[PDB]
Image (cartoon, rainbow, N blue to C red):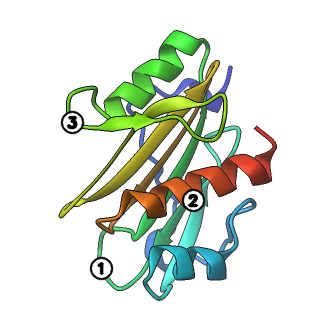
Amino acid sequence: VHDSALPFDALPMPPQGREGFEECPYLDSQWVADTNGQRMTGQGVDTRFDTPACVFWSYPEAPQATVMVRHMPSEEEAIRVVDWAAPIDTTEPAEEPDGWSGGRAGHEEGAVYAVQKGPVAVVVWSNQQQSLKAELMAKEAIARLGL
């Protein structure tokens, strides 16, 4: 079983939240602050997922960025994750890095970038309006994890 058999719509929940210290194994904290654009208050990891989910906080209650890696039982289920995070009628295609597919959107409420490749899904949410920020983070996580 992968990712503790969590359902398609599971969200990261690092157990100590914003007062956590534990760094993301695949994204440098400084790089994320510079890319996303807000100073870091704290960060945590959610090891329910085979690849831990990483959450990054600045001063707001809601995180500045959330990065989630999903290993689903099938490609169908990885697509369900991607379509949930980035709905077909509200987002534009995301096709990077090569071999990945899904959607992306940047609005006043934040941004998302969600792609799958086979049964693996990678979703990044940002509190920023620029979907490019979420895209850079997704690409970087994918590169660092060798996915």
Measuring 64% from the left and 18% from the top, which residue is drawn there? 118
Measuring 43% from the left and 84% from the top, which residue is drawn there? 38
Q: Which label sits on residue 127?
A: none
Check contact, mark 3 vs mark 1: CB within 8 A: no
Secondary structure beneath dot 3 equals loop
Q: Which label sits on residue 137?
A: 2
**Few, some or many residues within 10 Å of mark 1 (<14, 14–19, 20+):** few
Give the left or right position of residue 132, taking residue 139 as reference: left
Disc 3 and disc 2: Cα gap in Å? Answer: 21 Å
Q: Is residue 127 visible?
A: yes
Please state the horizontal and vertical placement of residue 55, each as a whole percent of the image.
Answer: 51, 63
**Few, some or many residues within 10 Å of mark 2 (<14, 14–19, 20+):** many
Please state the horizontal and vertical placement of residue 73, each as a whole percent of the image.
Answer: 61, 14
- Point out the tag, 2 or 1, that comes first from the N-terminus: 1
Secondary structure beneath dot 1 equals loop
Give the left or right position of residue 107, taking residue 85 as reference: left
Q: Which numbered disc, 3 or 1, marks the residue closer to the eye?
A: 3
From the image, tell me which residue sits under label 1: 60
Please state the horizontal and vertical placement of residue 114, each as a whole percent of the image.
Answer: 46, 39
Residue placed most toward the observer, 123 or 47? 123
Secondary structure beneath dot 2 equals helix
Disc 3 and disc 1: Cα gap in Å? Answer: 26 Å
- Point out the tag, 3 or 1, that comes first from the N-terminus: 1
From the image, tell me which residue sits under label 3: 90
